[PDB]
Image (cartoon, coloured by chain):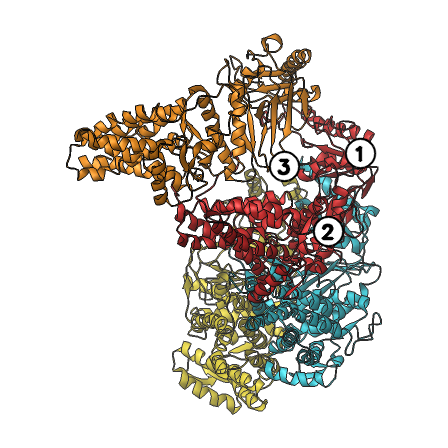
Chain colours: A cyan, B red, C yellow, D orange
């Protein structure tokens, strides 16, 4: 018999070990004091990637022979419906495995124990019916629009002091982006500087390049041009200007290298040109400006369409950047974030991305549950009764699944800056009482009414995680006759 | 000549160790709650090969120095007559070796113990034409088409939580396939996503490739072109040099030649009404612009295995140089289209006039467990083809094995000297199988042995090992049956294979390399 | 992904060691007795670079595996806003790590302590707004212009013999600079010549080139031509040239020899291979021009006429562009004995140039010499006991961090630091804002009389930077770098 | 390596060690239950050779420094005269060295003992004409063709279950081979598919090659063409340089010349009706297209040994340049087809007018054991031809050996001791064969030797060792007899082979080793 064939302690052990390694990096990731991690791999890579977004980093690397890559793969499917909030789904699945060592002690066919997954099914649907849910989300909405879930996504981030304001801003972006238009060209970049808003909302696309030191500082009623013996050269210079002056051209964007002679002309003319502009920015721009047909210098007049509300290069603080705004279409937009400048700040890139996808499905699902772990504690109180009442080893299955839910309250609290045991202690009493609105308040250090906060979780997050968490655990109970394995 | 010299007992030890190692990995697999395990090999494979079928996994890799690969090789010949169901045959041979320690204490000649192997042929009587087996297999059959044996083969396999449905599907595939044709062009692939059914049973042949973004979405009344030689043209055997030509107007001569190559492809193609072009290799860029405007869909670097299968299905192609079109090419016309299965974009060839060959498509939840379907798929194809045309089956769950065991113990004493001891050791070899079935179950093996024997001795052949139950039950209610053929060949298989292990050192042939 | 992984107690230690190593090198660089440090590297380094200014040397090199480069990187953003004065911000951030040993003694959760940083948010108020004052820096100002902060800024620098005079000069530059809105046109170079003044203030831009050992010395009502393309034909250049009255030609590249004979007879001074960077500033200065082919003259070119001449300075002969109409851009020229200490001036100026531009805009400053530093410590001690407690242990620890600064300033000076710290606190608690550490005295004295003051901006930004940067350290692992192994 | 450091008596030891090493390996080979051995070597070999025939493996390899190959080399001359049957002669020679230890304490002139070999001719002239004999074998013969000695040759080999049937087949092969025509063109190969018969008789020659994917599947009324020179054209007597052409304009002239080679082959081909072309070497690509359209099957790189044999079979041909077709070549037109032996593909040439040369194809149930058939077949082919030609035989199963042993023991003692001691040592040497026959039989050796001697001493020549019985039985009833020639020349040759052993040490083959 060839190859390494493992199922029993052998499969379970490897599954066990894969889950424990992932949980330690991820646990610090969740909540207000969530920690940013940068990964550098020695060999076959040359830089450190900053991602404290659990979904993004896990997808990127297939580090070991032990099983975990497939478990990792299913999270992204989750991340398109809701996906986000905080990365808690992976952590819960991992701890479920730890009780399995206890299971070897009971030394029997563990498949009967598989009933825990059945238990997961009732518990999953139970949280889909029991408690209070939002009835709002009218469309546009005066202020139930945000200050809610994005804030919870933001809760996972330290930057959430001035930032909670920024989170509010993201819904304005979604309100403009809904209906017939698809969830297309959305661009966000953080910047160096300090103001009350700590962010500006553009009515257009944001780019980072400059023609040269010479040229007009900014342009208004702007026109945009996008392009795919020495005396003879001058003819190229003049044709450009002759076509240029009549239009009133204010800005030129070129995907590739730009010839030096025209640069001189642009400065005097009052026209801003961009050398080697990135192609991806351009495609988003075409949808935004109304598009144009890009070919040879014949491109001018009406083959070119150009929006003109306002194009300017503005110092936001440290580094100069160029702002395109006021697109007539409204389908494609850009949001500019600001911060104190840290890896923790790059964390915000995750948060907003997390926020845009969630609202798209918030209107479509018309269903939500309370955030801050309110949903999770309530399920736990109900499941505890269930374990003892049922007969057999089935009860063992049911009891272990129930205690898994305990960690979410603990994980949010641990990164809070407050002691988890007391938190776990106080939290359970409130939820048991039958008070659904009450949950974990990171800001107050204890428990409070999150309805006021407005924090809510989208309906899709609870149903996909609970059913799919099974892969981590199914491997555990296929059989447990305990023989070999190759631990790590 | 060439060291590694072993004889008698020294030879037995290398042999003895190989048999014990194989049994523990394979033991887990047998029965309704069997085992599926993930294989990593590193350096030359770089992926997870989790295999349920003992036969499939054993053939793929020759892991170590001790001899066992040859014993493994023999199982496939058994498979190419049926040798599947649930893997049990390898285990019987392994336990044969344990009695050998007993044999040294015997103090007789060890090589007429070997004559015991002819006894194994005699043992064939116990499992052959002994006990009623099955009825049915009318042809096309309304309800006996499946939900029987495939389900049991699958029962030992984990995938059966959703795969038991897949198993039912496979006989539909055999009904279309069976006839004087024999067994060709059955193409089956696994998909990285899907629905509850987890399989879609396509009308014809399924391939996954696209010409490029520019080109028409569908073609109908389709013509198919297959070429041995690529579209690419230039260098030949001898470059003649990397060239620049002596002036301005001769550069044009080389450029012009490329245009002709374009011209031949369009002129021949348009008359035929060419809907799709499939080439097993690199495709030259110039023709690609042409195909888009024409309304023709081409496939770059199509796999040769897919192409040959397609040729049988379409009606064949004579694959030569650009003269290849019109009648040297036989094109079947129905529909060729690129469709999305439910996730990834694939191209479907269907509506084949021949009808001889068909394609099965599988879908899943994206895990190690999903790749399980790929291996189990191979396992399923073998069971169903044989079950319908052999018109014979035996009760599963080890029911057949215990009944045989009761009769064999009696036989050894009955014979006189030399014949008696050899045959008895073979007889006890049947006893481990009941134990192996129960052990993977998660239920107590010792309890199982005494209760099991009592039901078989009594005469009720239906009773067997019920893993779901944890005790002994009625096998027939389950619908668990084993192909008749697996038992007939295994008895012959075990006899020749078991003593291979008793004579060992390092056995021959592979085919000259 | 692989990497090197450290967490909670072990990760903190690596952070701990990086902070302590930096503080010892930087501590010697504070106040009138600051020590000059010299460094050498091989590969992309050409020669020994010696920098008093902590920010300049730290930015240049990421020497080893331990984490510290990002903390270091941050100080420069502060520098554009102000940064300098004396390097102390790095020291305060470093010492806050010492209380971490105390945190293990706490034995619970390091995150809760982090609340003190919020308490610091309350700060940047009580430090300077309240407690210590400076009422002045009204605008331009007759005598508070200098003989103040620059002297302290240069105190850390050994140059301060002749150099303190140089420092006085720097505030004159700010006065012209203030009004329009922002800094982006100041150029500073050092010369190999020597004089008591040790510096000349140029009303325009300074460049170091000559046409050749021929051509007129002086041009009048000068017109300036800048060309993108090289001169590498004779008649076209002269015909266009004569009509303009062309006094000087500057080309950013190789120049062709035939033209050169013509320029001398005409009475036109040309510059060969003038650096592009100098030219770009000149364009803003002179109104700019479009530097095209030989169609360049007349209208596409703009020229500023005042005085362009070659004048010897000390030893070397330099060419002076001056009298710019715009007024936005100005050039500072420094001269000295000619030693690594002289190069120290290059390090030293990027410590005073930035401060002054900011001094007019803030309209606020604080007394220097650590006067602000001890007073803030007295105020913060009260805060720890008043806040109920979680925010208190953390807050008290921050307060004691301020105690080291008085000690570091004294240590540099050549006096017993504890005695110094001791005498210092009594004067600050008294209510006299002006009183501070007088290193020359060896005791405490009136900071205002010898003039030292610190920009308001340095203290308010540092509080935000030192604190927030320090907390990222406890949670952050690996830090951006190559890290093979 | 310089000085061996062995002295006079120890010189004897090197001979002594060589004899003991060889006897154990050959020991399993003898008698109805024998073991098959596989050898693996690195250094100018290939992949594992398996030899049941002791003579074949010993002859092929010069493994080590001690003397033995010269003894070994001798067995082949025996093989031409008779050879095979079972390998026993090597075993007896090795045994005689064991008594030499007894001889050292026998403070007696060792060379006198040599006279034993002088009287070893007594075994030579006494075994001959005083025991058994065969007098039949008329020619072809209805039942004496086999089911005799070949079965005995096979008996030494375990395969005797399915295999004894195969041995019977071999005589059919010898009968067709007999007449005034010569010993030419015999070829045997095995197939990996199971059948009870395990063999098929092919009327013609078997080869395994094909023209390509295109071409008619089979041909009928076939004409065969063999070429001494390759289809490839360019080199000629004078190369014309290794050039090509300075552009692609002038490339056309060279290409045109190629077409003429294509034309000559078709013109000559069509008139003849040519159905198959066989060439021993590389085949040029251009003609390949021609053959497919014409309907002619050609073979690329055909092996020369098969070809030469084929020529005798087809009536032959004169192979030279392309002038070679029509009358210069003679072809046999019965049937040439590529047929699948239910498994691995191969091509069959059949219906030869000459009848002089024929080929045997064997099929295997599934094991190492049927490569054994290659091993076994060689033994069966040679033995039967000898039985008819010699017109003499002796009883098998060791019947001959015990009788002679009884006769030898009396002569030594009753003659003068100088000639007596030598003779007596020789006598007990014959004793081991009875022991080895029983040893591989399955019964205790001690009991067997004892019961054996009493029956032979009494006077029944027919009685011998019945391995199936485990005791002594009537040899004649089982039909086992040994060719008279195997006994006749072994006694003479063994006597002169053993003599070279005691006196001479170091000896071996060629240098580099």
Q: Which of these two is toward me, A63 or B479?
A: B479
Mark 3 and mark 1: Cα distance apart in space: 70 Å
- How dense is the environment of label 1, judged by Cα within 10 Å: few (below 14), some, or many (20 and up)? many
- How dense is the environment of label 2, judged by Cα within 10 Å: few (below 14), some, or many (20 and up)? few
Q: Are marks 2 and 3 in contact (CB under 8 Å)?
A: no
Tell me which chain the residue with mark 2 is part of: B
Q: Which labelled disc corresponds to residue B168?
A: none
On the image, the x and y values in percent for residue B466 come to: 65, 62
Q: Which labelled disc corresponds to residue B344?
A: 2
On the image, the x and y values in percent for residue B100 come to: 45, 52
D71 versus B19 height, above or below:
above
Q: Would residue B407 appear left or right of A337 to someone viewing this image?
A: left
In the picture, residue D321 is in which quadrant? top right
Mark 1 and mark 2: Cα distance apart in space: 26 Å
Q: Disc 2 vs disc 3: which is toward the camera?
A: 2
Find numbered disc 3 in the image and state the secondary structure of the residue it sits on.
helix
Q: Is residue A46 visible?
A: no
D370 versus B468 height, above or below:
above
Tell me whether marks 3 and 1 sit on the same chain.
no
Q: Would residue C195 appear left or right of D356 to someone viewing this image?
A: left
On the image, the x and y values in percent for residue C158 come to: 42, 69
Tell me whether marks 2 and 3 sit on the same chain.
no
Tell me which chain the residue with mark 3 is part of: C
Mark 2 and mark 3: Cα distance apart in space: 71 Å
On the image, the x and y values in percent for residue B171 come to: 74, 48
Mark 1, residue position = B274
Mark 3, residue position = C235
């Amino acid at each position: 018999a060839g190859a390494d064939e493992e199922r029993a302690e052998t499969a379970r052990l490897s599954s066990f070990i894969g889950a424990i390694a992932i949980g330690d990096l991820v646990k610090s990731t969740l909540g207000p004091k969530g920690m940013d991690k940068i990964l550098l791999s020695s060999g076959r890579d040359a830089s450190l990637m900053v991602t404290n977004d659990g979904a993004t980093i896990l997808k990127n690397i297939g580090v070991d022979n032990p099983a975990a890559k497939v478990l990792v793969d299913m999270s992204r499917v989750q991340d398109d419906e809701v996906g986000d909030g905080t990365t808690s789904v992976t952590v819960l699945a991992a701890e479920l495995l730890r009780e399995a060592e206890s299971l070897i002690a009971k030394k029997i066919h563990p498949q009967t124990i598989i009933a825990g997954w059945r238990e997961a099914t009732k518990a999953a649907r139970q949280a889909l019916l029991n408690s209070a849910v939002d009835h709002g989300s009218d469309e546009v909405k005066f202020r139930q629009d945000l200050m809610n879930i994005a804030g919870t996504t933001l809760s996972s981030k330290l930057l959430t002091h001035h930032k909670d304001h920024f989170t509010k801003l993201a819904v304005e972006a979604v309100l403009r982006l809904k209906g017939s238009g698809n969830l297309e060209a959305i661009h966000v970049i953080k910047k160096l500087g300090g103001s009350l808003a700590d962010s500006y909302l553009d009515e257009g696309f944001l780019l980072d390049k400059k023609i040269g030191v010479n040229q007009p500082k900014r342009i208004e009623n702007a026109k945009i041009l996008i392009a795919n013996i020495e005396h003879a050269e001058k003819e190229k210079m003049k044709e450009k200007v002759e076509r240029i002056l009549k239009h009133g051209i204010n800005c030129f964007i070129n995907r590739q290298l730009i010839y030096n002679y025209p640069e001189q002309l642009f400065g005097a003319a009052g026209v801003m040109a961009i050398e080697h502009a990135d192609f991806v920015g351009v495609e988003r721009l075409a949808l935004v400006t109304g598009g144009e047909i890009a070919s040879t210098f014949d491109h001018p007049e009406l083959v070119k369409l150009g929006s003109c509300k306002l194009i300017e290069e503005v110092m936001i603080g440290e580094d100069k950047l160029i702002h395109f705004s006021g697109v007539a279409l409204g389908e494609a937009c850009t949001i500019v974030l600001r911060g104190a400048t840290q890896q923790i700040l790059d964390e915000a890139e995750r948060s907003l991305h997390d926020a845009l996808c969630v609202l798209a499905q918030t209107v479509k699902d018309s269903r939500t549950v309370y955030g801050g772990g309110c949903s999770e504690m309530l399920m736990a109180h109900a499941v505890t009764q269930l374990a003892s009442r049922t007969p057999g080893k089935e009860a063992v299955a049911m009891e272990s699944y129930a205690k898994a839910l305990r960690m979410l309250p603990t994980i949010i609290a641990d990164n809070a800056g407050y002691d988890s045991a007391d938190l776990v202690a106080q939290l359970r009493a409130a939820h048991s009482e039958g008070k659904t609105t009450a949950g974990l308040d990171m800001k107050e250090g204890t428990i409070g009414d999150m309805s006021v906060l407005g924090i809510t979780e989208s309906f899709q997050v609870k149903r996909q995680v609970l059913l799919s968490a099974a892969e981590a655990a199914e491997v555990i109970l296929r059989v447990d006759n305990i023989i070999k394995a190759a631990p790590r």
